[PDB]
């Protein structure tokens, strides 16, 4: 009796929609919900002063105008940065290109008017607390990040910080995960009432050998392909559902962000997709009349 098996089909904005909007910004998130996304996917790191901010990389270089590790800088240092400084529609964030490539560079900083309905703070690195305040009713998928693949304490620390904040909200409509299994395990010990999805080790043990993942796991969040191996296949998704696990599929290089690819995944009975183009997926789901939570529609299986 797992309520996430009934939550389908989900349009989960990947970082708010990294190809249609500046990733991990209050703008991208607010936009993504207005377009009808069922859930927000985001990434969290911590500042020098133990503040959980929403940002994927461990450095601010790629998505902003600054430099250095997030853990190395004040929250006030990082809130001043232009979090759309390198955003190009259809290409996420690529620095070092002609300045007219970036339609939102400069609105955070005050040199260009914000789009109708938004203020400059909507284009900075936000506190996770701010996002939770802005979306009290919207479910949030939260991935724990670290500063390096060898710096395991940094993951463990963010998991400690995340459990505290999330316990204070008294909400349980989250899914918390990370690539680092220890970090998920540490989070599950400190916040046992928050749903989780396993790390790579848990994922591989379940996928390659059938070892059921950590208790409290309520979905598997998988790429489409991994090192040449097709992961989001109907046969695998059939097996996960049989064991009582929802399946959410992300892309981010492992497969295109296509109409065709999205449709393959929908047809494979995935319960949620994590698109870089969430507006696109909405159009696809609406045209196909696919069932959504609380909305009538057809089941692809
Ligand atoms: Ca992520």
Image: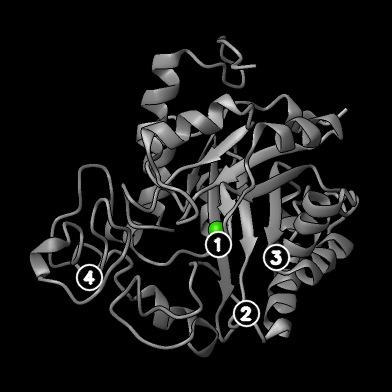
Q: CA distance from mark 2 to mark 1?
A: 15 Å
Write down the residue under mark 3.
162
Specify the farthest residue to the front.
Answer: 228
State which tag comes first along the sequence, 2 or 4. 2
**Secondary structure state at the residue bearing disc 2:** loop
State which tag comes first along the sequence, 3 or 4. 4
Asked whether residue 194 is in view, the answer is no
Q: CA distance from mark 3 to mark 1?
A: 11 Å
Mark 4 surroundings within 10 Å by alpha-carbon count, few (fewer than 14), some (14 through 19), many (20 or more): some
Q: Residue at x 77, y 58 (%)?
A: 204
Q: CA distance from mark 2 to mark 3?
A: 10 Å
- Figure colour scheme: one colour
Write down the residue under mark 2.
50
Quarter of the image for residue 296 reads top right
- Judge: label 1 CB < 8 Å from ligand 1: yes
**Callout in the foreground (4, 1):** 1
Tell which quarter ligand 1 is in.
Answer: bottom right
**Secondary structure state at the residue bearing disc 4:** loop
Write down the residue under mark 1.
43
Write down the residue under mark 4.
109
Q: Residue at x 41, y 28 (%)?
A: 282
Task: Establish if 275 lies above or below 65.
Answer: above
Q: Which residue occupies the foreground of this view, 85 or 164?
A: 85
**Secondary structure state at the residue bearing disc 1:** strand
Q: Which residue occupies the foreground of this view, 184 or 109?
A: 184
State which tag comes first along the sequence, 3 or 1. 1
């Amino acid at each position: 009796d797992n309520p996430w098996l009934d939550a389908r089909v989900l349009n989960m904005a990947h970082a708010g929609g990294e190809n249609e909007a500046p990733a991990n910004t209050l703008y991208a998130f607010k936009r993504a919900v207005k377009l009808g996304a069922n859930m927000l996917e985001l990434d969290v790191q911590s500042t020098k002063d133990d503040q959980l901010v929403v940002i994927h990389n461990a450095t601010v270089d790629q998505t902003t105008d600054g430099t250095g590790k997030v853990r190395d800088l004040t929250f006030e240092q990082v809130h001043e940065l232009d979090a759309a400084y390198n955003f190009i529609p259809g290409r996420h964030a690529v620095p070092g290109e002609p300045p007219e490539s970036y339609p939102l560079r400069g609105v955070r900083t005050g040199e260009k008017k914000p789009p109708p309905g938004y203020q400059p703070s909507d284009f900075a690195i936000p506190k996770l607390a701010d996002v939770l305040e802005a979306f009290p009713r919207t479910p949030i998928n939260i991935e724990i990040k670290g500063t390096s693949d060898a710096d395991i304490p940094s993951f463990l620390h963010n998991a400690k910080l995340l459990a505290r904040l999330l316990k204070k909200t008294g909400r349980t409509d989250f899914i918390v995960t990370s690539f680092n299994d220890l970090a998920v395990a540490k989070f599950h010990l400190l916040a046992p009432d928050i749903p989780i999805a396993p790390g790579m080790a848990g994922l591989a043990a379940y996928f390659l050998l059938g070892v059921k993942p950590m208790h409290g796991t309520v979905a598997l969040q998988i790429p489409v392909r991994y090192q040449g191996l097709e992961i989001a296949t109907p046969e695998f998704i059939r097996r996960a559902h049989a064991d009582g696990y929802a399946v959410h599929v992300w892309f981010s290089g492992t497969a295109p962000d296509d109409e065709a690819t999205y449709n393959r995944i929908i047809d494979s009975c995935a319960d949620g997709l994590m698109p870089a183009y969430p507006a696109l997926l909405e159009r696809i789901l609406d045209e196909r009349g696919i069932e959504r939570p609380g909305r009538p529609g057809v089941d692809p299986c």
